[PDB]
Image (cartoon, rainbow, N blue to C red):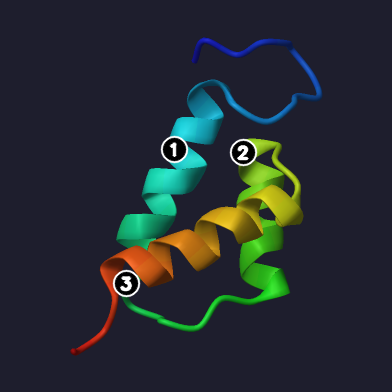
Amino acid sequence: GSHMARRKRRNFSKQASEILNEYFYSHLSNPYPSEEAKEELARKCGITVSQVSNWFGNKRIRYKKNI
């Protein structure tokens, strides 16, 4: 777990490491991100859709599709 607090949390931490990498493995199926998608990750990991959005753009630009 290694949670910073019993309730409510900020960016970074173990949850942050998984919100990011999990998206890399879970958004492969669906190329297009959405507020609902960011919101789901934001809620389970305790991060804000804005920070979540930062990864979403990053994972899509790093993976790339066709060249």
Q: Is mark 2 on a helix, strand or loop?
A: helix
Seen from this angle, which residue lies furthest front? 67
Q: Which of marks 1 and 2 is nearer the N terminus?
A: 1
Q: Residue 41 appears at what percent x and percent y?
A: 60, 52
Instruction: Give the vertical position of 20 relative to 16 (above or below).
Output: below
Q: In this view, does 39 lie to the left or right of 14?
A: right
Q: How far apart are marks 1 and 2 (CA)?
A: 8 Å
Question: Which sits in the foreground, 51 or 14?
Answer: 51
Task: Give yes or no for contact between labels 1 and 2 (Cβ–Cβ under 8 Å).
Answer: yes
- Which numbered disc covers residue 33? none
Numbered disc 1: secondary structure: helix
Q: Please rate how many residues cluster around mark 2, counting C-alpha atoms within 10 Å: few if below 14, some from 14 to 19, many from 20.
A: many
Secondary structure under the numbered disc 3 in the rendered image: loop
- Three-letter amino acid code at the position of disc 3: Leu
Q: Mark 2 points at which residue?
A: 45
Judging by the rendered image, the residue that carries numbered circle 1 is 18
Q: In this view, does 62 lie above or below 14?
A: below
- What whole-number distance in Å separates the C-alpha atoms at marks 2 and 3? 19 Å
Q: Which of marks 2 and 3 is nearer the N terminus?
A: 3
Amino acid on which the number 2 mark rests in the picture: Cys
